[PDB]
Length: 25
Length: 26
Length: 26
Length: 59
Image 1 (cartoon, one colour):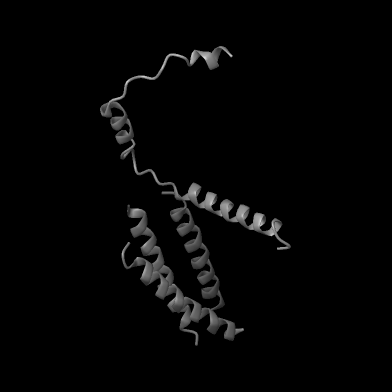
Image 2: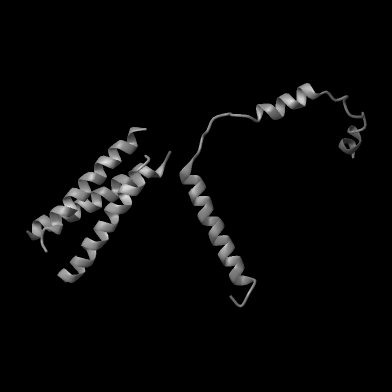
C-alpha cells in the first residue's frame, strides 16, 4: 500500500502548479 | 491505522478528480 | 519513511495555506 | 418647518436626455467584484436567517 505516499506527492505538485496557473491572472 | 491511510488515499483520488474538474476551464 | 510522511504533511499544509491566500481576494 | 416649505417651487420640466443619460451612466463603472466581502456577507445572511428561523419557531 505504501506507494500512496508518492501519489500524494504527485497530487500536491499538480495542485501547486494549478495554484501558479491561477495566480497567473 | 493504515486502513485510515486507505481511506485517506481514497480521499486523495477524489481530490484529484475534483481538481481536474475545477481545472477543466480555469 | 515516516519522515517522508511528515514531508507529506508539510506538502498538505503548504498547499492549503497557499491556495487559501490565493483564493482569498480577487 | 423652513425646509418643509423650502420645497414649494414646483418641479422642473422634464426631458429624456438628462435623466436617460444619468441612468445610462449607471452602466459599466468597473467590474470590481470582491469575493471576500460578498462571501462574508452571504455567511452572515445565512446566520441571521438561521437564528431568525430558530427564534420564530420552537425551532
